[PDB]
Amino acid sequence: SMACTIQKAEALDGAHLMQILWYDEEESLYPAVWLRDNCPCSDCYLDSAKARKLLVEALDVNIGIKGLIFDRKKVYITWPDEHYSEFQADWLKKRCFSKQARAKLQRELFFPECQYWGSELQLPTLDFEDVLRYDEHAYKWLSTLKKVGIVRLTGASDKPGEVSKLGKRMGFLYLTFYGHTWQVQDKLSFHTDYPALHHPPGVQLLHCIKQDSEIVDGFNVCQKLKKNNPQAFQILSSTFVDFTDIGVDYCDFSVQSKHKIIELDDKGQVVRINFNNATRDTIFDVPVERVQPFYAALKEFVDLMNSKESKFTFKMNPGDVITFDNWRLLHGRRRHLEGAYADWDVVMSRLRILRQRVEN
Amino acid sequence: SMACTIQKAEALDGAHLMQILWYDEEESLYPAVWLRDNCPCSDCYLDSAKARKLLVEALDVNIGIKGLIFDRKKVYITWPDEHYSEFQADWLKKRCFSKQARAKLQRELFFPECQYWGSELQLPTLDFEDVLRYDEHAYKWLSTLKKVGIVRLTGASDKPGEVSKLGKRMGFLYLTFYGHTWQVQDKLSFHTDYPALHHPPGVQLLHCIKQDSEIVDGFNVCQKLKKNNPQAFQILSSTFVDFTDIGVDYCDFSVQSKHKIIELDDKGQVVRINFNNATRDTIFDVPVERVQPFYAALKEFVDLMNSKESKFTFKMNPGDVITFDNWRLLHGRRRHLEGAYADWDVVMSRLRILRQRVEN
Ligand SMILES: [Zn+2]
Ligand SMILES: [Zn+2]
């Protein structure tokens, strides 16, 4: 490939930078300290663990390249203390520091693609055994979960054990916490689950053993709220609300956290909704004048969730396994289920592995 | 008590506020919407679950008090739709919206007191069985963990099972994740544990079965860094670093996250350090010019950790159970241990419960 072959490589700027001219005619710049830190030799790097052995205390932050050789596919660098490093062209190209290359790689790692929905949702559906058996189907399943926030699996048995069977096949680890002490447990006001936790459970897997649920796309609701009621959006995305879960589950517990109901990342993108009205504390840590406008904003948020254009209604049949993003969807309803929760890290892990397996 | 008895109560500002004059001569202001939202009657509130039954859609955000009666200890309110609410004086007083009362209550819920340390640390120590048996001792144990970041328990057996025994007695739930699939598992470069997780494990419990560890107070290090090297502190508290844990543990896994090495809350206070050099990815999602100054800053951070004034050294003896804050401490060392991790929510829960039991 023209994009991935080296036409020229040289040290620049007191040898503190390496510039690559690709046959593509594209150009890339690599800091010497980063190349040294990421030497793939066996003194510096453990292949089997994919881990860096090099210590920060061994790294000269003012290092420059002493000598550089290249061909079409490799760069060969000598350091001032005679350490020697070889870098592959493809490895360098992927890790290029341009905004375009970095953003491309981030998309590949974190799967940010998102499809918003409302009442017009076609509930994504795949066969249970297909997902159990074949990488392509398991991959479709998880990528749809991440993109859409919900996927249905049909054709599981109507017997207990299917959630555990699915977990084992996927290599999932399931969460336990107060109110959900076992990995798999038997199960109108829209809510997310367990906002009293500092890190609410990411993904829920529900299996219908014996048999309406309503759901909204929280990210879609937030986007409409920001447009129609910007001040409401500002209040809900900036006000820390106390959530409190007090009870007994083999022991007495008092689980408490503060969350913004609309949780944004550094770029102002919604990453989680934290909302259960039952669990919202009587304790409200805001100046008195902030209180009534907070409730006005909450009312607008909840009005939007209850609007006909937002809500999707569905019925769970025996053998259905529904999986959903508890950070994104809110649910409610106006029954023998088995359910488990997983951390998003476990699900994203599987998504990454499966994508690699499908691509090969 | 003079502070907690009502000299006068009245509706103000179109009945949208309730003002309380305490016999103390202090004054408090309560929004009508918040009083309505927090009606303790059995239509609105579930005592046993300590949960609100009232729906957001049933709450008039523009509500005002229709009628108000009071005595020394209670307020009796009638709403415009004839709903009726009684509030206790002590309950109101505690939930007062003044900055002083709110901050007091937050301290009581979240235990923010923090004692920084270095090489001069006297390792807090309590007896294992004492902690197992008596609330006062268990309370001292957990409050010291939260304040100091580390506590040693002495006088456990030198046999396996003590971590599990301690967990059961405390009603703890233990975490599992890739690299630590069992609740209790057998176990120089300063690091925190498992930063590749979006929510790294909060608390570690280590029990020495058969027998130097070094530790630093990460919060103390950050405070010194901010003072001596403010630009380094700024870089480390604002730059998202990729952490990556790839391997096999019953299944193939690829766990990945981005963290600021120095993680601040909204008020600029350090809440977590996320740092393991082995796990820090080769992938670095920053503009090229940001790279070398990041490494310079990291080097200053690590230099500070390795300085003689920062490091505390100790040896684990058989029967020792060491507990520490994995969000705060970094550790390393230049051996038969059993270990478990817990979420801070589980530990804070126990701390709250124990404080109430000790106070009674
Ligand atoms: Zn090397
Ligand atoms: Zn009521």
Image: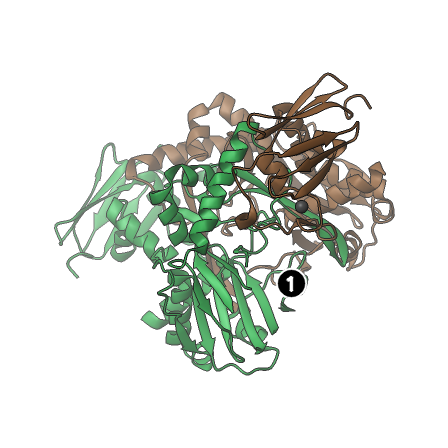
Chain colours: A green, B brown
- Quadrant into which the C terminus of chain A falls: bottom left
| Residue in the image at 35% along x and 39% along y | A33
Q: Secondary structure at mark 1?
A: loop
Query: Chain letter of disc 1?
Result: B
Q: Residue at x 78, y 56 (%)?
A: B162
- Using residue B260 as the reference point, say whether residue B327 is left or right of it: right
Tell whether B153 sits left or right of A321: right
Vertical order, A320 against B16 (above or below): below
Q: Position of residue A207 (x, y in %)?
A: 55, 73
User: Label 1: few (<14), some or many (≥20) within 10 Å?
Assistant: some
Foreground residue among B101 and A353: B101
Cβ of mark 1 under 8 A from ligand 1: no
Which residue is depicted at the point 54% across and 80% down? Answer: A318
Quadrant of image for the N terminus of chain A: bottom left
Q: Quadrant of residue B236?
A: top left
Closer to us: A134 or A292: A292
A271 shown above or below B80: below
Say which residue label 1 marks: B182
Determine which quarter of the picture holds residue B6. Answer: top right
**Residue at point 62%, 25% (across, down):** B98
